[PDB]
Amino acid sequence: MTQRSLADIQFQTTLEGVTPAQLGGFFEGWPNPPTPETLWRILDRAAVFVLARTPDGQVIGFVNALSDGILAASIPLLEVQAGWRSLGLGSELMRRVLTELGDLYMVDLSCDDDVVPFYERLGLKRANAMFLRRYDNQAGIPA
Amino acid sequence: MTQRSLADIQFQTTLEGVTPAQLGGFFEGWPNPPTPETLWRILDRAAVFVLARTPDGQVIGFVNALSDGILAASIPLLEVQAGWRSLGLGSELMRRVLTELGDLYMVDLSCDDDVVPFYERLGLKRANAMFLRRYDNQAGIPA
Ligand SMILES: CC(C)(COP(=O)(O)OP(=O)(O)OC[C@H]1O[C@@H](n2cnc3c(N)ncnc32)[C@H](O)[C@@H]1OP(=O)(O)O)[C@@H](O)C(=O)NCCC(=O)NCCS
Ligand SMILES: CC(C)(COP(=O)(O)OP(=O)(O)OC[C@H]1O[C@@H](n2cnc3c(N)ncnc32)[C@H](O)[C@@H]1OP(=O)(O)O)[C@@H](O)C(=O)NCCC(=O)NCCS
Ligand SMILES: [Ca+2]
Ligand SMILES: [Ca+2]
Ligand SMILES: [Ca+2]
Ligand SMILES: [Ca+2]
Image (cartoon, each protein chain N blue to C red):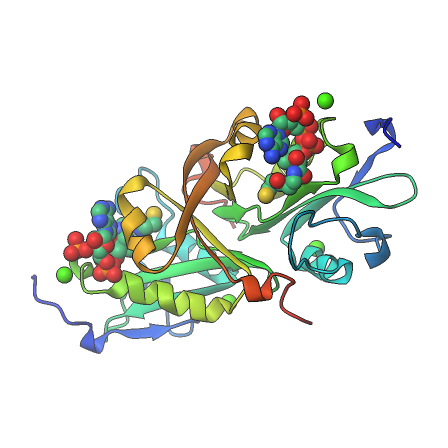
């Protein structure tokens, strides 16, 4: 329950063929996570996103992005399920979402100190993220 | 060419009655700024935005936001024209755009060290912003 290969991971940028039943297992460590159904809606409302799927259709990594298509984009969420980390998938998802976004002037995201090096190795630079967290709505605004 | 009052500043969240001719004077300090026509398109593509206007219809402050309406939003641009700063307008624009966004779990933005206190006084907290700047496209992706 340990050996892995990225060789039969496939990527897609639509929800065609993806059900909420295939979006379970995310939000590791979140106290009150969006459900898989809510994740599906989050993806549907993103400007762009990238999914990494095993052959059975389970989504084991994703990234989403907000964008105006003209000047700016931001990347709210990036996650690879723990058994699939350390293979380069997170970096690959980031490269793929940047391709989907195009060469916009600004692409920005927030992170904690521990993951700064992950992002620096992708070429991102570091400034201040000012933020709000409305923890009552951590599971998402309902439909 | 110095006295000001916010008393006849009006706010709006649509482009009704706003022309590109009324969106001049922004991007102070930018080497290759979006034109007013491009700014109009940026606003039109935002999830939400707030404009501050004088009685003649000139826009003298704005803020925009990207959002998925479910979990996350980000604020790419905030600017008040220099003769209108130091009256509370920037803070007011921020409060108004947060109202337009609603109580989403995440609201995030990037900034330099100098403006951190402005954002802390609005209740925002500080983390790392990881970012890319594609300076060739500073004036925006064309229509
Ligand atoms: C960050 C994340 C997406 C990286 O995915 P990944 O597929 O392992 O990415 P890569 O294989 O390209 O890079 C992995 C490297 O990133 C670094 N890294 C990732 N998370 C780290 C952390 N929390 N602390 C320290 N280093 C970290 C490590 O150098 C790691 O290499 P290692 O496995 O040899 O230690 C993954 O760790 C994850 O899903 N974490 C939980 C959610 C998260 O923190 N996402 C970031 C936005 S909040
Ligand atoms: C940041 C900005 C929007 C604030 O607008 P404003 O209408 O003056 O906002 P407020 O009146 O609510 O707050 C002003 C206070 O913010 C702080 N502040 C704003 N910019 C600052 C800066 N560059 N360095 C230090 N303090 C700053 C000061 O405390 C200032 O008070 P002061 O005029 O008495 O010195 C305005 O300075 C601006 O348009 N700057 C250029 C664009 C920008 O930096 N926007 C931020 C996103 S990049
Ligand atoms: Ca879509
Ligand atoms: Ca490894
Ligand atoms: Ca609109
Ligand atoms: Ca003042």
